[PDB]
């Protein structure tokens, strides 16, 4: 009786004071960037790139917050699906995974659209 799927009740407390006070800077940036808007990104890969926000939030392969951005040319690293977990829809070397602090919104919206 009583099937199983997803539990974790203690985590609810760990992600309240520990994953809130220390991750207040990353959260403020993660809870600001909109989805589906052209934004720039900075990294040691090569140079500045231009893509659109696809996913914004926590991850499975890495902790903290993350932001998915797709580019027109082959300037990505991941392929959307990392370690089985999928975020966006696109081929490889197109949708790179950076952080809010690493992201830069250039054209999100005046209010909503």
Image (cartoon, rainbow, N blue to C red):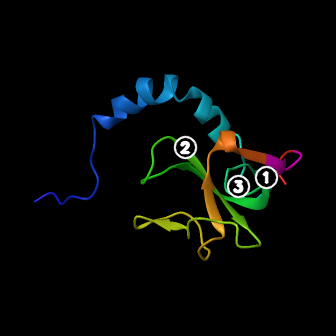
Side of 106 where 42 appears, left or right: left
Q: Which one is in front, 8 or 85?
A: 85
Q: Residue at x 67, y 56 (%)?
A: 45
Label 1 environment density (alpha carbons within 10 Å; few <14, some 14–19, many ≥20) = some
Instruction: Classify 89 as above or below 50.
Output: below
Image depth: mark 1 or mark 3 in front: 1
Identify the residue at image location x=45%, y=30%. Answer: 19
Q: Residue furthest left?
A: 1
* Along the line of sight, the residue nearer the viewer: 75 or 26: 75
Locate residue 79 relative to residue 1 in the image: left or right: right
Q: Which comes before the other along the chain, label 1 or label 3?
A: 3
Q: Provide the secondary structure element on which disc 3 rests.
A: loop
Residue 52 percent location from the top left of the image: 75, 61
Residue 113 percent across, percent down from the top left: 85, 54
Crowd band around label 2 with a 10 angstrom C-alpha radius: few (<14), some (14–19), many (20+): some
Kindly identify which residue carries mark 3.
35
Magenta range is: 105-110
Residue 68, horizontal then vertical, whole percent: 63, 57
Q: Which one is in front in this view, the residue at disc 3 or the one at disc 2?
A: 2
Q: Secondary structure at mark 2?
A: strand
Residue at horizontal 56 percent and vertical 66 percent from the top: 78
Residue that extends furthest to the right in the rendered view of this protein: 110
> Residue tagged by mark 1?
40
- Inter-mark Cα distance, 1 to 2: 17 Å
- Res. 31 visible in picture: no
Residue 103 vs 81, above or below: the answer is above
Query: Does residue 75 belong to the magenta stretch?
Result: no
Pointer 2: what residue?
A: 65
Measuring 42% from the left and 53% from the top, which residue is drawn there? 60
**Contact (Cβ within 8 Å) of mark 1 with mark 3:** no
Mark earlier in primary sequence (3, 2): 3
Q: Quadrant of the N terminus?
A: bottom left
């Amino acid at each position: 009786g009583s099937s199983g799927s997803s539990g974790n009740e203690e985590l609810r407390a760990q992600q309240e004071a520990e994953a809130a006070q220390r991750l207040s800077e990353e959260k403020a940036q993660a809870s600001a960037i909109s989805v589906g808007s052209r934004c720039e990104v900075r990294a040691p890969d090569h140079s500045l790139r231009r893509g659109t926000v696809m996913y914004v939030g926590l991850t499975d392969f890495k902790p903290g917050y993350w932001v998915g951005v797709r580019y027109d040319e082959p300037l990505g690293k991941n392929d959307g699906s990392v370690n089985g977990k999928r975020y966006f829809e696109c081929q490889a070397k197109y949708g790179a995974f950076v952080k809010p602090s690493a992201v830069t919104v250039g054209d999100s919206g005046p209010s909503s659209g």
